[PDB]
Image (cartoon, rainbow, N blue to C red):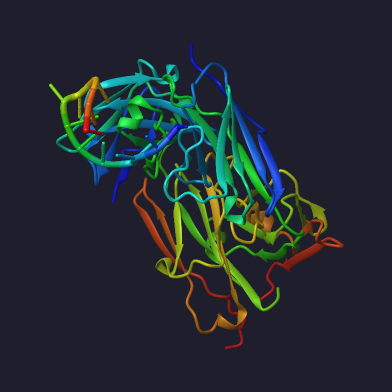
Amino acid sequence: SDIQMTQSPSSLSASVGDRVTITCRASQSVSSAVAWYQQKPGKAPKLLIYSASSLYSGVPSRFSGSRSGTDFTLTISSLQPEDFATYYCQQSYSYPYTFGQGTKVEIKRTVAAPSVFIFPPSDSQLKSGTASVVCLLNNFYPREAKVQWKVDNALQSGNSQESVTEQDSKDSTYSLSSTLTLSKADYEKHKVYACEVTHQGLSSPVTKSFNRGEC
Amino acid sequence: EVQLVESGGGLVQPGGSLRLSCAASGFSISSSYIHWVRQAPGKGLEWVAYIYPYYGSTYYADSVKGRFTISADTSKNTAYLQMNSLRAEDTAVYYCARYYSSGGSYYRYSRGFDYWGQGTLVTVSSASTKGPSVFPLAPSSGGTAALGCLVKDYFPEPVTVSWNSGALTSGVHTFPAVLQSSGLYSLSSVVTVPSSSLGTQTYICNVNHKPSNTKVDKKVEPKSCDKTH
RNA sequence: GUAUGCAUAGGC
């Protein structure tokens, strides 16, 4: 039957300079044929290790791996901001060549507050009969945050969606984008459009608002 | 100079069929073991199939077995993945990769996949191709100012956005697209710039949605509030 | 546990 590679932990967070160990266990004997890959978000995986211990050309010295029995370990000696990625093992012993489910490595850094911006709908969009209002939370940490829309003090729920970027591989920060969508009709029936941001680097919540028909 | 390039991805209806191409340069496919690996949205990697063109040996993962076969064309130095009876779960990015066929690959363990393609997205859906609209996000914090494009109501993925034809890179964030209740995608691309530069420098959103052949250059500038002129 | 190059390819 098919060989299973059980990789742990599912995810981990560790600071710069730390040693990190990701482990992988084969459900059967893979006899040392194991590779490790690094995958940056939206990008092709890159080969790190190819036998259980061997370093592929061009791969930094901080990456190593070793085998005892069916247990396999990948080791990053000093974590770098560029090391943010998902890390996968794979066995080449017997087809199908199975991957472990992966380990996403977040890099800890010092707390940073989101810079908040708010964007009123374009005139162009309005004539389509829709209004989109975008609240931008730029370059913050940790990833948890909260955005709340208020239209004339009425809290908006179920009409927005948000999206977060992957951890930056230099400053290790995050960025968030939230969009409130309304019919034009409902848009032009109100005045104050605001977004309130809750995060740790903020001693008190920040609000960024506009008034419809203002400039 | 060794490279692999995927082609043939795109929108396909359930039960339909698709043919992906993996085109090799800087080596002959006969010298390598060519694999296909796929990743469903927010999912791990899944090994699906491989061909070794010299022998002609192949294997298929159960998930794709009997619906998918792989073929080698040495004349075009390309491998093809023929996918039939496609299902919604077959929706994923599809990578071709290789390992070189070396003494070590055979007698020893060097099988790790050294060269990968960039990937190609395969969306299995009944829904219809639709192009985006592009709307400005106009700047009005500190010594910096933020502006961007809102790329709204398109399908399927992907959409690519660059700034000033790719001249402007630092400062940029393009956010993961979101699926709305309509069934269409929306994303925003934002750039923070020195507020000093709003007069001087031009900012242009370059939007490309390949499925619908829609390309848009959107110039973003702060809005002007007079009205007395 | 070493050559992600070659090669009737189980050898160099």
Evaluate whether residue B179 shows in this view: no
Judged left or right of residue A132, residue B14 is left
Residue furthest top as drawn: A1
Q: Nearer the viewer, residue A88 or A54?
A: A54
Residue A114 occupies which quadrant of the picture? bottom right
Q: Residue at x 75, y 62 (%)?
A: A112
Judged left or right of residue A120, residue A89 is left
Question: Is B213 rendered above or below residue B31?
Answer: below
- Viewport quadrant of the C terminus of chain B: bottom right
Residue B64 occupies which quadrant of the picture? top left
Q: Nearer the viewer, residue A163 or A139?
A: A139
Q: Residue at x 47, y 42 (%)?
A: A55
Q: Nearer the viewer, residue B144 or A63?
A: A63
Residue B148, horizontal then vertical, whole percent? 55, 65
Q: Residue at x 24, y 47 (%)?
A: B26
Question: Is B90 rendered above or below residue B145?
Answer: above
Evaluate whether residue A203 shows in this view: yes
